[PDB]
Image (tube, rainbow over all chains, first blue to last red):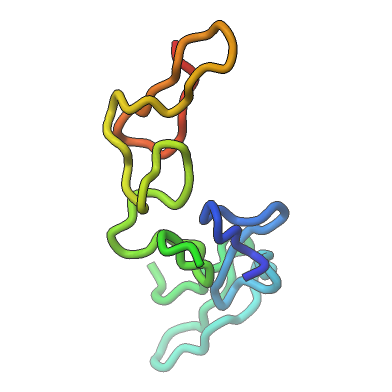
Length: 59
Length: 59
């Protein structure tokens, strides 16, 4: 994993995230990108620009 | 291989307290008062604090 130092279990320099639908090449995907389509009567889920994790439920 | 770290997620493996460090042994903290640095000059030795993997400079 280029995003993770396996020795220390710390993110490598420049890396913001190690995995996630809102992580691309160790960087956060931009705020607003649709990362999960709603199955029900809900809006779609979008990256926050500040996490590699795509939202799973609306508050 | 680092048994203490899942490099795909950059998370510690199940059961692990630490991944690296002079106060880490087999992914677990060494006990408080373990000597973690034998001073090479005139300072005091440094000691593990029981709850962290690093080796802090003796106050």
